[PDB]
Amino acid sequence: AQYEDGKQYTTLEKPVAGAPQVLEFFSFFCPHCYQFEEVLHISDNVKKKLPEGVKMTKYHVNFMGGDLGKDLTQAWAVAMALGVEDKVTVPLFEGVQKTQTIRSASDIRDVFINAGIKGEEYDAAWNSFVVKSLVAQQEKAAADVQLRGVPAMFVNGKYQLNPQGMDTSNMDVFVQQYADTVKYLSEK
């Protein structure tokens, strides 16, 4: 067929109950993740094709970058809590991987301050239990899909995107196929 298990996607041996409809894992330390978001715009292209009322969820992961890596999962939780994902995603990617001016929890915070988030507001979120459970949720989710690498995307807690079995030559063909595969999986 056009879409094949083992080709554009794989099936989790152990489907995840109550999972987000579309779940992406990434790290701000992840070079392939930089390409995914800042150059290929996978998240955006996937959303531009998703059915009505399908939410795209994006989680950060700890295993890259040690202490800074976890700080970034906590800051991403802050971004989710405050609903400012679309203001901090680009300067966080660039701060870690382009300018490399993000080297500490303070430098991360600077990105938010400069993007318009009040200091009190950031700090209150940062220290909050709401943010602590969001961190736990993201770690939880990584465990539930038995995550081994990023970037990754799972659909309805059942199917795993397999960019390796897609056409990798034209950037835009690749991106279109990835986005089309997610749409197909979402209606499956």
Image: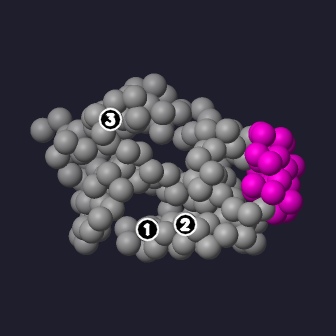
Q: Position of residue 183 (x, y in %)?
A: 28, 37
Helix, strand or loop at mark 1 = helix
Comparing labels 2 and 1, the label whose residue is closer to the camera: 2
Residue drawn at the location 24% of the way across and 53% of the way down: 6
Helix, strand or loop at mark 3 = loop
Ranked by sequence position, the earlier of labels 3 and 2 is 3
Comparing labels 3 and 2, the label whose residue is closer to the camera: 2
Q: Verify CB contact (< 8 Å) between mark 2 and mark 1.
A: no
Q: Residues within 10 Å of mark 3 (few under 14, many from 20)?
A: some
Amino acid type for the residue under numbered disc 3: Leu
Ranked by sequence position, the earlier of labels 3 and 1 is 3
Q: Position of residue 102 (x, y in %)?
A: 83, 53
Helix, strand or loop at mark 2 = helix
Residue drawn at the location 75% of the way across and 56% of the way down: 122
In the rendered structure, find residue 134 and report the number of the disc placed on it.
Answer: 2
In the rendered structure, find residue 50 and report the number of the disc placed on it.
Answer: 3
In this orientation, which residue lies closer to the viewer: 130 or 28? 130
Specify the farthest residue to the left. Answer: 1
